Amino acid sequence: AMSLENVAFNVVNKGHFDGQQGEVPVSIINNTVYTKVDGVDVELFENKTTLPVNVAFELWAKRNIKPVPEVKILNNLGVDIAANTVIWDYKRDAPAHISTIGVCSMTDIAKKPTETICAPLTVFFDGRVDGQVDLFRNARNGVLITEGSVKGLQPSVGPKQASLNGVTLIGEAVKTQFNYYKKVDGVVQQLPETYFTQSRNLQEFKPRSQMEIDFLELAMDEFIERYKLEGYAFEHIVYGDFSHSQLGGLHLLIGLAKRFKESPFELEDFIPMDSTVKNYFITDAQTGSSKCVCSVIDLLLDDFVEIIKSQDLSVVSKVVKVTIDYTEISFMLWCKDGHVETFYPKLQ
Amino acid sequence: AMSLENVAFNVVNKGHFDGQQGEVPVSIINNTVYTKVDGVDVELFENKTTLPVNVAFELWAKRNIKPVPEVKILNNLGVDIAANTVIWDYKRDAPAHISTIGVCSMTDIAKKPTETICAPLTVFFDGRVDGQVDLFRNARNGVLITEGSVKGLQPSVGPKQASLNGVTLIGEAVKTQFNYYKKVDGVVQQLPETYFTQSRNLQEFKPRSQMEIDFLELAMDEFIERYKLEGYAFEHIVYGDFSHSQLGGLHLLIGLAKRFKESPFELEDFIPMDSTVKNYFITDAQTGSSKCVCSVIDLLLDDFVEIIKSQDLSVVSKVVKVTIDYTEISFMLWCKDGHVETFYPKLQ
Amino acid sequence: AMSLENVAFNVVNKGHFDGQQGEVPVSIINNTVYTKVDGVDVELFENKTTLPVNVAFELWAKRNIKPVPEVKILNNLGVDIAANTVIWDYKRDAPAHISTIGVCSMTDIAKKPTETICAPLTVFFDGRVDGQVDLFRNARNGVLITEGSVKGLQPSVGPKQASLNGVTLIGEAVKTQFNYYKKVDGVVQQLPETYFTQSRNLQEFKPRSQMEIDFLELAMDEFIERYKLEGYAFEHIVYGDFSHSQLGGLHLLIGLAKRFKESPFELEDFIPMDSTVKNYFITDAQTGSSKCVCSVIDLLLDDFVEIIKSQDLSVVSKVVKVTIDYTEISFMLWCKDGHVETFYPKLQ
Amino acid sequence: AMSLENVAFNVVNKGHFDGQQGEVPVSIINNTVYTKVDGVDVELFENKTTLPVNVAFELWAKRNIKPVPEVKILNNLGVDIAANTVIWDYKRDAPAHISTIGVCSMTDIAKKPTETICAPLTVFFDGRVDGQVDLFRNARNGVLITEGSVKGLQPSVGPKQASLNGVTLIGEAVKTQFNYYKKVDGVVQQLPETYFTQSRNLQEFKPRSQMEIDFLELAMDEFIERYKLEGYAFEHIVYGDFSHSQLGGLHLLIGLAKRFKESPFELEDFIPMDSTVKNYFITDAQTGSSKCVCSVIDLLLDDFVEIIKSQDLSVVSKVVKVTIDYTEISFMLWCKDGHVETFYPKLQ
Amino acid sequence: AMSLENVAFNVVNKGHFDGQQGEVPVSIINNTVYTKVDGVDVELFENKTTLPVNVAFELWAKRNIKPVPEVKILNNLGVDIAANTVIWDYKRDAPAHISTIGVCSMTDIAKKPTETICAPLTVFFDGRVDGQVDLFRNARNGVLITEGSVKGLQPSVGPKQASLNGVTLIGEAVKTQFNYYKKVDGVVQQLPETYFTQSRNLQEFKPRSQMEIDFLELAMDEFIERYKLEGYAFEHIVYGDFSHSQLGGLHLLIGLAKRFKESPFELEDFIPMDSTVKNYFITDAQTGSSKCVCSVIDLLLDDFVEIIKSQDLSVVSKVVKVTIDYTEISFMLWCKDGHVETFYPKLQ
Ligand SMILES: N[C@H]1CCN(S(=O)(=O)c2ccccc2)C1
Ligand SMILES: N[C@H]1CCN(S(=O)(=O)c2ccccc2)C1
Ligand SMILES: N[C@H]1CCN(S(=O)(=O)c2ccccc2)C1
Ligand SMILES: N[C@H]1CCN(S(=O)(=O)c2ccccc2)C1
Ligand SMILES: N[C@H]1CCN(S(=O)(=O)c2ccccc2)C1
Ligand SMILES: N[C@H]1CCN(S(=O)(=O)c2ccccc2)C1
Ligand SMILES: N[C@H]1CCN(S(=O)(=O)c2ccccc2)C1
Ligand SMILES: N[C@H]1CCN(S(=O)(=O)c2ccccc2)C1
Ligand SMILES: N[C@H]1CCN(S(=O)(=O)c2ccccc2)C1
Ligand SMILES: N[C@H]1CCN(S(=O)(=O)c2ccccc2)C1
Ligand SMILES: N[C@H]1CCN(S(=O)(=O)c2ccccc2)C1
Ligand SMILES: N[C@H]1CCN(S(=O)(=O)c2ccccc2)C1
Ligand SMILES: N[C@H]1CCN(S(=O)(=O)c2ccccc2)C1
Ligand SMILES: N[C@H]1CCN(S(=O)(=O)c2ccccc2)C1
Ligand SMILES: N[C@H]1CCN(S(=O)(=O)c2ccccc2)C1
Ligand SMILES: N[C@H]1CCN(S(=O)(=O)c2ccccc2)C1
Ligand SMILES: N[C@H]1CCN(S(=O)(=O)c2ccccc2)C1
Ligand SMILES: N[C@H]1CCN(S(=O)(=O)c2ccccc2)C1
C-alpha cells in the first residue's frame, strides 16, 4: 500500500523509507514536500531532480543507506539500473539511475530483475542482500558487489572507500571494500587491472602514504630531490604555476590541498556530478592566475608517480591511456628533450 | 487510510472520491496531478486554487455530488465551513470554504462539528445525511438544509434551484428546493422574507413567466404599454441605452439576453465568483457603448416589476433595500417629477 | 545542427519543424516558449506535457503532419514508440509516446529502430516513408501501416478515419484508410476481425447510415418498431433513462447526440485521453439525473444492433467480449425472462 | 501613492485602474493575482505576459479603455511606446509595448515623453488627451491620432475601426475613425495612400458591400461571371482548392468564411499576434486538404478585386507591393498565357 | 549560429562560452538548465535573475572572465551597458546591465557600440580588447579602462583591485589596476580625486598598512594613544559599542573583522548588491547588542583617519561629503565640545 502520506510518515518517523505503516498530512508546493507538525508546515524534501516532486521524494526516501559503491564506479562499469534499491547520487541530489526495479510504481520497469526487460540492462546486484549473488548468476548483464568470496567467480578487489549516506569513507565499523564482478551477455568478464581515485576533499585532505606526508610537509625542491622527480615537471603538474594569467598545471588533488593551506582559491564545478576526472574553472585568489578547464584527479601520489615514471618521454605530444576506477582515462603527455613538460588527464 | 494514490484511484475508477480501496501511480508537476495510463501521463486535475495541488485535488475529489445550495446562498447566510462535505465552487474552480470538518487531514480544523473550534463558525449541515439535523440542533452557529419538516423548526422555503456538479437546475429526477434554517449564537433565527435570483445564463436564457415571454417577443414600446410601465424607466434600466459613450442602465439579465440575440457584447467578469448581484465591464460590439461597472441581477421580470412598482417616486435620490437570496440588496432609486430616471443594484 | 532557436525558426517560418536552416530569438518562461517579434514576445508554445518545456516544444514541432492512426488504435495494438516520427496526442496535448527514435536528442533511445534497445518495444512504422516497410520486416516487435499491399504480408483493413493535425476525418484529398500489420517476438500476428468506433463528436454528430438517420429523426417507439428492437432495452441503453437520480443507460454516442439536441448536459471527461470506450461523469441539466461513471462508445448504430442481436438472452448476468478497434471490449449483458435489461461496455 | 493593493482596490471597485484611493488584501501565487472576498480567494488576474505578475497586473489595470488603434496599425507605423497610457494587446494578453512613460514605476523609462530617453523612440500620442498634440509637435519621433484637424498638420484618414476593450468595432456611440500623423527624426512624414484590412472574424463574418453579399450568396461560377473575374484565378485564390493533399489558395478571409458555413476546418494560429497578413496551418475537416503556411488577409472583396485587376498579367512570377494598413505588403503574382495562376500575400 | 545547445556545449567543454562549434542535449525545468551526461541530467545553471532562464544562461556563459572593474565602480561612474561583453554581477548572481551590445540576440540593443541607440548610453569600453580605445574616442558617452597610457587622454588611476570570476583581488599574475577615462556628451571628463574602498571580506580580512596591523594587534587604548586619536570617537565608530540594546557605531570593516576574531555576529545583507557603502542588520551573538541599519564601509584605516582628522568639529550635526569609488558619499558628523560623538556613512 504505497502512498505519498506513507512515504512521508516513514521519513518523519524512521529518517527514511522503512516499510512502516502510517500516514502524515502532506502538502506539495512547487518542488517541495511539507508535512504538518502541530499546525505548521515543515519541509521534508526539496526536489533538485528532473523527476516529478512526489516521485523524487519517494526515491530519495527509498535510497540505499548501507555503504554503496561511489556513483563514478557504477558509471565506469556501465551500470544502468539497480536491483530493488535506489543508489542516491549525492553529487547531483538525484537518483543515480533513471529507472528502478521493485522500488517505486512511477519509475519501475519491472518488479524483479529476472523480468525480460532487465536482461539487456547492466543491473547492479548487492551480494549483501539475500538472493542477489544468485540473481547475478542468472542475469544476462550485471555488476555484483560482495564482502567475500563467490564460488567459482574470481573477484576484482574494488576501492577501499564506499559512499554511506553521501559520505565517502573507508569503513572501520562497516565494510566499504567490495569484490566486484561483472557479466556482459551471460559471460563473466575479467575486470581489468586498475588504479583507484582516492575520493578526498580539498578542505579535509589527509595523506595516505609517506610520500603524501612528505609532499605536504616538505618544500617543493626538497620533495622532488627526495623522490628523484627531476625532469618529471611536478613543479608545473602537481605544485601548480601561478606566475602567468593562465594557471599552469595543478592536476592532482594533493597539490590543490597543499596550495589551499597557504592561500585560498575558487573552484567552479561547472559539471556537478561524480566522475573519475573532475573539470574546474579555477581562480587563484592570491595571484589572479586562472584556468577555464583545469582537470583534476585525486590519485594517491605514489600511483601518479608510478604512472608518469612508466612512460616513454621521447615524443612531443602523445595520448597515455590509464585504467582508473575501471575506466580508460586519456592523459596528454607533452615532452621536450627527454623531460616532461606537462601530463594531464582529460575529461571526456 | 487516506492517500494521494488512493484519491487518484477513486477519481480514475469512480469519477470522484467514493471511499474505495486501491492505488494508482501519480505524478505531481507544478499545479497538475497526472496518472500513468499504459505508459503515458494523463491529466487528472489542474489546481486553480490557492491551496497546495495535492490538497486541492483531494477536496475536489471529495466534492459534494448531490444538488447543493448555490455558493451565493451559502455566502449570503454567512456559512463559514461545511460539516463532513466539500461544497465545490465551480465558478472559482475552488472549495467554497477554506477549512473542512472530517474531510481532509491538511484542511480539517476538526473531525466532527461538535468540536469546540466549530462553535463560533457557521457550519453548513445537510439534513439529507444521517445525524446532521441533530448536529445543527447542537451547533452554536449553523445553516441547515432539509427536504422536509424538522419538528418544531420554522422553515424558510429556499430557491427552486440548486447546483448539481456545477450545473444549476430545478430538479425533476432529484429534489433541489430545500428548507433553510439558521442559528446564530445558539439561537435559531427567523430568516427574512426574500426574492430569489433565477441563476440563468446569457447564452441559454429561458423565460419563466408570460411577462418574460412578452419581454423577449414584443418590441420595447408595446411591452411597456401592455404592462403599464410608463414612467418606470424600463427603456434605460432594462432595455439599455446604447446611444452615448457610457452604456445606460442594462441591470436586468433578461435585458442583456434580449440585446444578445440581436447583437453581441463583451462582459468582463472582473470579480469571478457567485454573487446575487454581478458587476461587469460591458462593451457593446455594435455601438461601442461601454460601462466599467455595470451591476446585473437576474430577477424574474415580474419580481423586478413588483419591486419598482412598490416604491415612492417623490424623492430625487434614495436607497431602496430589497431582500434577495436572503441578503439585503441596496438599490439606488433616482426620480424626477414623479417618474423613475434610474433604479440600479449596488454590489457591496 | 539541432537547436531550440532552429526549432522556433521552423515553427515561425514553416508552421512546424521542416528541417530548414535558421534561428529566431527565444525566451523560455515557466512552461511557455516565446519568440521576439518586433520588440515584443509572442507565444509559440505552452507546455501541457510532463516533459521539459524545450523538449516538448521540439516534439510538438516535429509532430507527424500526415494523417496518422488515432492514438486509441495505436494503444490497442500495443505501440510503445514510433520510428523516426512523433505521433502527437491532441487529446492530451502531449506526445503519444514517452521516447523517440531518430527525432530528438533528449528523448531518443536510438537513432534507428534497428538498434537492439528497440527490439523488445513495439515500434510504429509508416509504410508511406521510404525504408519503413523493410524496417518492420527486420523489427522484433512492431506495427506497420501502409496505403497498399506488402508482398506476402496478410493485411488488416483499418478504420476509414485517421487523425490529420488533430482532426479525425475520412480523407477525400488524402488517404486515411490504412492496412495494418503487427509483429510480436519476430512473428507476424493475425490481427483479429473487428468493429471500429466512429470517432464522432457530440456537437457535430452526423449519421452514417439510414438506421442512424431514422434514430435521430424518429421518436423512440416508432424507431424500435421499425427496426424490430422490442425486448432489447434500447429505451434504457441507447435513449437513456432520466427519471431517477441515477441516469440509466445512455452508452451509445448517438443517444447522447439525440438528447443533446433537445436539452443540454454536462460530460465530465475525468480521464482525458483517446480510448475506444470513454467514461464520463454525466449530469443532465433538464432533470438533474446523473451518473459518476457512464461508459460511452461511438459504434455505428447498425453495428451495435448486430452485436446485441447476436447474443443469447437466457442468463441473468454475463460478460460479452467484442473486438472493437482491435481490442477486446467487455460488455455486461443483463437479462430477465428472455429480454435485455441492460448491456454496457466496461472501460478497463 | 502607487501600490499593488491600491491597483487591486481599483480593479475590484472600478473595473480597472481609475486613480481611486483604497486598498484590498491581495495574494500572489505563481502568475495569478487574488483578492480575499469574504474569507475566500477570488482571481483578479492571470499573467500571460513575460513581465513579473504584479507588474503585468498594474499595466493591464492601467490599460486604455477608450477606442484605440488596433495593434497591427501601431506596429505598421513603427510605434515603440505610448505616452502616458498602456495599449493592451488582447490578441497576446499582454502590453503592446515593453516599456511605459508615466504609467508604472517598474516599466517606466520616463515620466514625460519630453525626456531625452524618448527622443529616439516612436511615441504614440493620443490627441484626445490634453497636451498630447503639443507633445507630438515637440517629440523627435512619434505617431499621433486625433478626432479632428490639427492646424497645419496634413492628416491621414485611418481605418473606420478601432479596438475598444479588445472588441474591434466601427463606433456609433464613440468615434473610432482617427486622423493619423507620424514624425521621423523631428520631421513630419507623409503617410502613404493605403488600403485597410477589415478586421473581421471567421465565425461572425459580415459582408460590407454588394460584391461581398454576392460572393456569400452566389455559387462560384455565377459570381465570377457577374463580376467579370474570368482569368483572375478566384477559384484557387479566393474560393480555395480542396482537391489535392496541399490546400490550394484560400488567401482572403471572405473565402474562408464562405467555406466555414458549409464545412468546418482547423486554423492553427502558430504566431498569435495582430498583423495585417495572418499565417495559419489550415486543415480542412471534410477533405483532409491541408497547408502548413496559408497566408490570409481580410481585405474588402472590392479592394482585392481592384488590386488584382490593376496588375500586368504578362510575366511568369513577380512581386506586387501593396500598401495595406500603412505597411508595404508583398504579394506573389504568378501568371501563364495572360491569366492569373495564383496571387498571394507574404507575411515577412 | 547561436543556440541554447551550443551555449551548453561550450559550458560543458570550455567552462564558459568560447565560440566553439557543437551541441549537447539540454532540458529546461523551471529556472534550471540541465544537460544529459550518459543517461542522467546534470545541472548546468540555476537562474537567480529576473531574465528568462535560457537568456540568463547565455549571458552568464558569455560573462567576462578577465579581471574587470567591480560593479560598484561601474555603477558609480554611471555605466549603463558594456561593449561586446557581459559584466556578471556575482553579488546579485545576475548581469550587471539590463541590455547588451553584440552579445545575445534577446538582450542586444545593437551589434556595435557605434550604433546610434548607444550614443546616449554610457558604454563600458575595455582598452585591453582591440579597437575599444578607438571606439571610446568616437563614443558620445562612455567609460574606458586601460592597462597603460592613452595618447592625449589624462588618466585616473583606479583601484588596485578588480573582480576576476567573482573573486576580488589585487593581481600578481594579471593586471587589476586600470586607468579610467570617462566621456560625457563627447567631452573627456576630469575624474575627481577619490578614495577607494578596499573590498575585503570579514572572514579573510588582511591589513594593508602598519596602522591596520596595529589596529588588529593592539588593544583599543594603546592604538588610540599611538595614533593620537583621542576625541575622534574611534571607541564608538570603529571598535563598536556593544553595551546597550542598540549596537553603537561599528562602521568600518576593519572593526567588524577585529570583533569577529573574538566573538561572532550575524550580518543580514538585506540589499544584496555591490555598493561602496553596505547596510547590514547586525546582531552581536555574545551580547545581544543589535542595529537594524548599520552602515559599513571598507576604507583603509589610514584613509578613514585622514578623512575624520580633516573635518571641522565645531557643529552639532553636519553632512560631510567624501568622494569614494568616484561617487559622493554623505557621512553624518556629530560633535559636542570640539570632539566627535559619531561619524557614519549613509547608503542612499
Ligand atoms: N523490492 C523491495 C526492496 C526495496 N523496496 S522499498 O520500497 O524501497 C522498501 C524498503 C524498506 C522496507 C520496505 C520496502 C522493496
Ligand atoms: N564491528 C566490528 C566487527 C567486524 N568489523 S567490520 O565492520 O566487518 C570490518 C572489518 C575489517 C575492516 C573494516 C570493517 C568491526
Ligand atoms: N570536457 C567535457 C567533454 C564531455 N564532458 S562530460 O559530458 O561532462 C562527461 C563526463 C563524464 C563522462 C562522460 C562525459 C566534459
Ligand atoms: N466525514 C465523512 C463524510 C465525508 N468524508 S470523505 O473523506 O470526503 C468520504 C467520502 C466518500 C466516501 C468515504 C469518505 C468522511
Ligand atoms: N425519481 C422520481 C420520483 C420522485 N422524485 S423526487 O426526487 O423525490 C422529486 C420530488 C419533488 C420534485 C422533484 C423531484 C423523482
Ligand atoms: N432575527 C433576524 C435578524 C437577521 N437574521 S439572520 O438569520 O441571523 C440572517 C443573517 C444574514 C442573512 C440572512 C439571515 C434573523
Ligand atoms: N463593487 C465592489 C465593492 C466590493 N466588492 S466585493 O469585494 O467583490 C464584495 C462582493 C459581495 C460581498 C462583499 C464584497 C465589489
Ligand atoms: N529521422 C528523421 C525523420 C524525422 N526526423 S525530424 O528530426 O523530426 C525532421 C523532420 C523534418 C525535417 C527534418 C528533420 C529525422
Ligand atoms: N488528389 C486526389 C487524387 C487521388 N487522391 S488519393 O489521395 O490518393 C485518395 C484515394 C482514395 C481515397 C481518398 C483519397 C485525391
Ligand atoms: N494470433 C493472435 C493473438 C493476438 N494477436 S496480436 O496481433 O498480437 C494483437 C494483440 C493485441 C491487440 C490486437 C492484436 C494475434
Ligand atoms: N474505469 C477505469 C478503470 C481503469 N481505467 S484506465 O486507467 O483509465 C485504463 C483505460 C484503458 C486501458 C487501460 C486502463 C478506467
Ligand atoms: N501619466 C498619467 C496618465 C496615465 N497614468 S495612470 O497611472 O495609468 C492613471 C490612470 C487613471 C487614473 C490615475 C492614473 C498617469
Ligand atoms: N453620443 C452620440 C452623439 C455624437 N456621437 S460621436 O461619438 O461624437 C460620433 C461621431 C461620428 C461617428 C460616430 C460617433 C454619438
Ligand atoms: N516620406 C515617406 C517615406 C515613408 N514614410 S513614413 O511616414 O515614415 C512610414 C513608415 C512606415 C510605415 C508607414 C509610414 C513617408
Ligand atoms: N512567415 C514568417 C516570417 C517571419 N515572421 S514574423 O516573425 O512573425 C513577422 C511578422 C510581421 C512582421 C515582421 C516579422 C512570419
Ligand atoms: N561581439 C563579440 C564579443 C562577445 N561576443 S560572444 O558571443 O560572447 C563570444 C565570446 C567568445 C567567442 C565568440 C563569441 C561576440
Ligand atoms: N606574468 C608576469 C609578467 C608581468 N606580469 S603582470 O601580470 O602584467 C603584472 C605586473 C605588475 C603588477 C601586477 C601584474 C607578471
Ligand atoms: N538606505 C537605503 C536608501 C536607498 N538605498 S538603495 O536602494 O539600496 C541604493 C543603493 C546604492 C545606490 C543607490 C541606492 C538604501
Image (spheres, coloured by chain):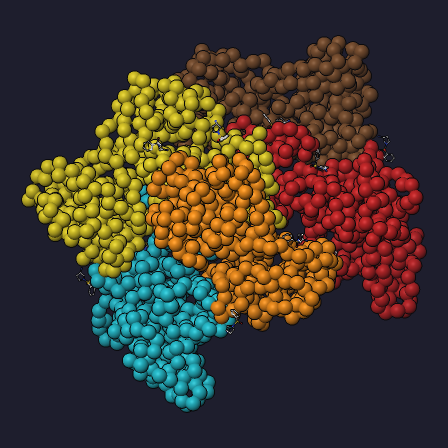
Chain colours: A brown, B cyan, C yellow, D orange, E red
Q: Quadrant of residue E131?
A: top right
Q: Position of residue A74 (x, y in %)?
A: 53, 24
In the visual, does C104 lie left or right of E324?
left
Q: How many marks?
A: 0
- For the point 39% across and 60% down, which residue is it? B91
Q: Give above or below for B11 relative to C64.
A: below
Q: Position of residue A145 (x, y in %)?
A: 49, 21
- Most extreme residue toward the left is C337
In the foreground, D234 or E335: D234
Q: Quadrant where the C terminus of chain E lies?
A: bottom right
Could one spot residue C131 in this view of the protein? yes
- For the point 41% across and 84% down, which residue is it? B340
In the visual, does E65 lie left or right of A9?
right
Q: Position of residue B21 (x, y in %)?
A: 30, 44
In the visual, does B266 lie left or right of C3?
left
Q: Quadrant of residue D147?
A: bottom right
Could one spot residue D30 in this view of the protein? no
Q: Quadrant where the N terminus of chain E lies?
A: top right
In the visual, does D43 lie left or right of A305?
left
Q: Give above or below for E202 relative to D137.
A: above
Q: Position of residue C189 (x, y in %)?
A: 28, 22
In the foreground, B241 or D58: B241
- For the point 40% across and 20% down, which residue is it? C135
Q: Give above or below for E89 relative to E312.
A: above
- For the point 25% across and 58% down, which residue is it? C263
